[PDB]
Image (cartoon, coloured by chain):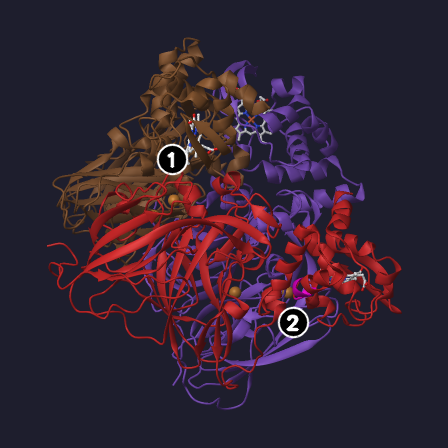
Chain colours: A red, B brown, C purple
Amino acid sequence: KLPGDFGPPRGEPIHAVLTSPPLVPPPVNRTYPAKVIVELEVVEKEMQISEGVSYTFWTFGGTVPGSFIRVRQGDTVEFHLKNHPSSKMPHNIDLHGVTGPGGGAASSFTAPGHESQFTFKALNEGIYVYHCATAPVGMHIANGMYGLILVEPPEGLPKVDHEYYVMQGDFYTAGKYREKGLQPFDMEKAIDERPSYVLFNGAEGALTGDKALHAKVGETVRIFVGNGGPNLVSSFHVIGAIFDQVRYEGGTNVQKNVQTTLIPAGGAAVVKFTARVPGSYVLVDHSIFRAFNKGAMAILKIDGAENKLVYSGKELDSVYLGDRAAPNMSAVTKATQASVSGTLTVQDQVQAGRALFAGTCSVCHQGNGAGLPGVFPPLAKSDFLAADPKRAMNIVLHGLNGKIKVNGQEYDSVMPPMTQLNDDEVANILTYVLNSWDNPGGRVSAEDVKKVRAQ
Amino acid sequence: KLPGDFGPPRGEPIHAVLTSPPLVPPPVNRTYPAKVIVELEVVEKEMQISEGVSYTFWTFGGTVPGSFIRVRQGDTVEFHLKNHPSSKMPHNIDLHGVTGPGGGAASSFTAPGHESQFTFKALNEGIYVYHCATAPVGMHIANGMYGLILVEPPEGLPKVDHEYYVMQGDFYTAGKYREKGLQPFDMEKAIDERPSYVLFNGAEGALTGDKALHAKVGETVRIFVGNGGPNLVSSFHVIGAIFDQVRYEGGTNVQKNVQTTLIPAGGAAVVKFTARVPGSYVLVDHSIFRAFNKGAMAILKIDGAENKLVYSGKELDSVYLGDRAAPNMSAVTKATQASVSGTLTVQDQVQAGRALFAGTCSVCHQGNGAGLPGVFPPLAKSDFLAADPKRAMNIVLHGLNGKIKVNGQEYDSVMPPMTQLNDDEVANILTYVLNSWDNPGGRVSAEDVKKVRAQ
Amino acid sequence: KLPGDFGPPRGEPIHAVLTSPPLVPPPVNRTYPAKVIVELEVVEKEMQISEGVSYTFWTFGGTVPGSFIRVRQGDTVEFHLKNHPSSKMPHNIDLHGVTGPGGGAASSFTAPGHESQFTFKALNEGIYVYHCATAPVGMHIANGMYGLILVEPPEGLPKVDHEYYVMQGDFYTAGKYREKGLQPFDMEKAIDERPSYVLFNGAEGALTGDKALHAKVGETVRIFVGNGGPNLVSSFHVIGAIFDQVRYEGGTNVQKNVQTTLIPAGGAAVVKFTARVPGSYVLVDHSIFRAFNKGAMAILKIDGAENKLVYSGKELDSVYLGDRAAPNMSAVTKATQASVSGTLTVQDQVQAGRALFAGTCSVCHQGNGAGLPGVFPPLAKSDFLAADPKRAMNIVLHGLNGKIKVNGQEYDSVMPPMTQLNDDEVANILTYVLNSWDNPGGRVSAEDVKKVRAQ
Ligand code: HEC
Ligand code: HEC
Ligand code: HEC
Ligand SMILES: [Cu+2]
Ligand SMILES: [Cu+2]
Ligand SMILES: [Cu+2]
Ligand SMILES: [Cu+2]
Ligand SMILES: [Cu+2]
Ligand SMILES: [Cu+2]
């Protein structure tokens, strides 16, 4: 008498409601086992992985992660996979939580333009990763082919104010982080488990600024958190808060009151958060260079009244979140498109630089370029800058140390090199600086920086 | 009054029954503390890490992982380590679960041709890794020097139908994955934690195809799962099933109903599985490139009657498991030996290619080379191939995209590059294709591919 | 009615007692919520990361990890951060366990020579990592900016005989492991998560030999264990013992009786150990190349009476712990300083080599250089060595195999290459060998080895 033994399906078959991230379908709200028909379509498509950076994703339902599936333990699921005729590759599916070889893989093999089906009973309650299972499996997963299926316990999950859907992935581009253009998959980097981006929901900034998740003080938030991998294990953490509960897959064990929790590659967890004070709460992989150098940050923004007895501090700003504190970086997308078309203006560069200056430069030189006299020199009306604007390229790329004088004040400090900035980025930041705070104007081009880097 | 306080040893000393993977000794089936004499011998020996790839392993008892040791909490263990006189290195042992400095290491130091002993009381119930503890410790572990010791609780573990022994390891060869010949240990790759192979039980295919583990529908299977490392943490997972229970070392905590669980480097767990429906269940490290590009897959094959109410799908096939869906790849071993002896025939190559074509090429071009008209072009009687057979080398190594015509049908798709295939592999796959499905015949050599790669 | 609801602060404000690793402040020993004033100062400073290897650390309170903070759940904490005027960078703080955006980060932003404050209520009991939150966050963390804050439950933790403070970190130097001199931060290695050192408490040997932690047989030891990262997840393990209990952050779950446990990047745990038999117990990251090739080993030394019924073996020695079995390696620091000043004598080299020979060479050739006739050849009065002393450089760097004769005995074995040793190390070890056991004398210089490596 297997687990999930709740009887044959009753009533009429139900068409599963699938939702796109970061949203989840309604709770099933039923007390009997059903036949649930799931229809999921694979689409291969270019999308923006970062501003001005395109990638050819392979997707379940048009999104990364793929559509969220929600059924009840004991349901019989008739699973239809369609492969869009525009696809170049064959695809299939392995759903964790399926009891059967391959989790569906052999019977769901689907060539472009075709459809397949298989039927399984959902014996196991829990939150589960599903992903493509087509050789080379790692390429298909790295291209975005993963999502979550929730198999509810028979009584349903406890009611909460909000449910969200967040899934980490590691991505492997031929180009470096934030190198612009259409970036191919990089098999070498993937085999070595050296990702160029580590992301929530398939893109840089997918869940930051104006795309943050929302709740209010006093409300409960449940997040279904997946780790599609392919390779990385997430040190999954919420900055400035705690999880009331963390439950992995369909495990009997529930951990309560933790802030940092390890999600295996291919793993999934349900976490619960209670909003206590207003502000922005950051979901990160706390393997910190992923969070702050490769894109692995998401925001849950809580609105409501401050409570100074609990926290007197200010909201998250660019000192910590860097260039993602702002609503968006659309100016970088505009500038990159303008360079492609050969139509790049000084103002395109100024606006792109403005977005990129936040955190990256403002932490020391300030948002207004004033610096701090004798500690951090000014960029606003800087004589040192105006004397030799082109030297700024070497300063950004290779740093500056030693005694210098700026606006009649001596400095003897260290600006670290910032060699990871791409040529266009250095060009744009510097064009912004040159055209702000009554500086001389002019501009630096991507090709100017390339030549200096090449020295 | 220390834990495991069950009295002085009683009766006569017992000689421990040690077993080679994937098998385990009988349950001790006793109710009193004994003196248990363990005799374990270190042997350094070349073995096949993959087809036609040899490696000089250092082993406890002739195998990787080493012999399984099984005692009862409260036993006094008199541990004898012998180092075979053919050994070049000194060796010793640290058993997790030992209470004492080094877990035995200082007193078990054993030069080639010598023997050592130390005595310890097994105070701690649990499943524990043991490994060599001889500087450079990481080299000794990376060479295969690890195994499991089970310290039973006093009542014994619950009875199950089968017990098996599976242990993950990361391996570091100078050559790339599947590069043939005797491969040295690569210290650089090891320090960087960049393994070339990630394996269960010391070899590719050690537990796949005809070497799978077995059980029947309705039966319980306990697996003692170790992670010898040296470096990697396993996202340990069973495809298409769930673990009833996962228990780490001798921990009081037992997790129930999970599919994916993180095993630390040097860690060990006891997992329980109940067979529900027939087919092949894959144990993997779900850091996916390990599982599908570096060897980290093992099979538990369940025989019995299908249950279409639980799973209507087909058994695991080469679309998912690739070239390990088949019983074995002995043809690759034969072809590699033939190249060594200068006796390599066309048929040796054809049979080696046949083994390697499964998954790697058949996912798109099909097992019969028919492809799918207008979506994947045919390899069977392909005019495009016959027009310029040597171009096939560039197609496999560097991919093909753009408009082409094959057997009177237009294609406009993408075949990704497969540059990770070694020269012999490309040669053999192509010789198989050229000599199948009424294609022109002939052959490609490893040296032909080398020259094209070198372009 | 939030967690930690124990009332407004009562009594007078308390000035927090902060302690430097590996020590912890006294238990708060109180039954009422207080206002606790914390004053923590950031200092940037060069320290020795290894013998003769300097690094510019950025520190909370002058140490890595930073000062330990100890408060009670329900306390109101008024947190003052001062940035020393000698600092070149701005700094701030995110304390895990804070309920509020950034964990303090925006309001604690502090330029060199300035001070900031924010107030928070400690609602969440547990052990928590705190770290700098200043862009580039990963650089600041990698430079040493992390520590632990304990928020006690209201009843206090159970009494133990000793409390200690241990925190892992991964470090990224431009130079290789044990390459001497002032080593810059290496951003490339950090982004790739390829550390050169992995350390407890900010240095090689910080907690080994004469800097070990101590307890006696029968005593309980609690260790507050942090993982500052920035990037690595620790397979945290105690060699030759077991943890009675492991509790992560403020989690409700407590695991009992485990030896190996995974600590997320940014995570923290409280572990408990009961001393049973005397000797040295090694805390390691069991991703083994970290422990034995990158510095990740710490010692808890237990004094008291042997108990041969539990463990008959000898204390940890250089076969396992290598060059850290000894009290210290101060001779290496002396020799490195002498080379800097151009004052390096033969004896400076001999004493430095002596320290480095332990484990690295003695495992095979023995502490007395006698070797083992016919198995490992002698270094003591070695004719083979004396015939061509300079050949020894190639033997250490590239290994030796094949038939050789030494002191009238034939050998046919393998000495692996040791290419990871730095030029000064090879020079010093060889100068030690040449000047010991009635060998001919003379010396090898760092520049001699460089030239041979360069071949
Ligand atoms: C703190 C860590 C800094 C960050 C981040 C950035 N800069 Fe910087 N900068 C900093 C210091 C301490 C100095 C003086 C170095 C010395 O030798 O004492 C500088 C210097 C400059 C200059 C030249 C001086 C001037 O015109 O004020 C320029 C043009 C400059 N810095 C620009 C710049 C930009 C564009 C940055 C972001 C990309 C940036 N700096 C980051 C400290 C810090
Ligand atoms: C799908 C992902 C494929 C896999 C895996 C392999 N091949 Fe392929 N191949 C595929 C496509 C879509 C195409 C057409 C590309 C285009 O420009 O439209 C091809 C082409 C070939 C050819 C040439 C055409 C022909 O003779 O049919 C050859 C000889 C070929 N492919 C061989 C080949 C081999 C040996 C493979 C395994 C090693 C292999 N292909 C993998 C799709 C896919
Ligand atoms: C065991 C793993 C060894 C370690 C660690 C080191 N040495 Fe070694 N050494 C070893 C062997 C088996 C041999 C003989 C190799 C053969 O071809 O049979 C050697 C040889 C030498 C020699 C030359 C012979 C002699 O003078 O005895 C020298 C000078 C030597 N080894 C030095 C040396 C040093 C300095 C080491 C530490 C840095 C060292 N060896 C490590 C085995 C092993
Ligand atoms: Cu796919
Ligand atoms: Cu999976
Ligand atoms: Cu060994
Ligand atoms: Cu160990
Ligand atoms: Cu800082
Ligand atoms: Cu943090």
Q: Is residue A451 left or right of residue C439?
A: right
On the image, the x and y values in percent for residue B225 come to 30, 44
| The stretch drawn in magenta includes residue C43 | no
Say which amino acid is labelled 1: Gly
Residue at image position (49%, 44%) is A193
Find the magenta span and give its range.
A354-358
Q: Ligand 7 falls in which quarter?
A: top left
Query: Which mark's residue is nearer the viewer, 2 or 1?
Result: 1
On the image, the x and y values in percent for residue C335 come to 71, 42
**Image vertical order of residue B452 relative to residue C274, above or below:** above
Residue at image position (27%, 40%) is A106
Residue at image position (42%, 12%) is B442
Report the front residue among A337 and B155. Answer: A337
On the image, the x and y values in percent for residue B183 come to 47, 25
Say which amino acid is labelled 2: Glu
Report the front residue among A420 and B300. Answer: A420
Chain for disc number 2:
C
On the image, the x and y values in percent for residue C365 come to 53, 28
Q: Quadrant of the C terminus of chain B?
A: top right
**Image vertical order of residue C31 relative to residue A237, above or below:** below
**Image vertical order of residue B181 relative to residue A415, above or below:** above
Q: Is residue B175 visible?
A: no
Classify mark 2: helix, strand or loop.
strand
Residue identified by numbered label 1:
B295
Classify mark 1: helix, strand or loop.
loop
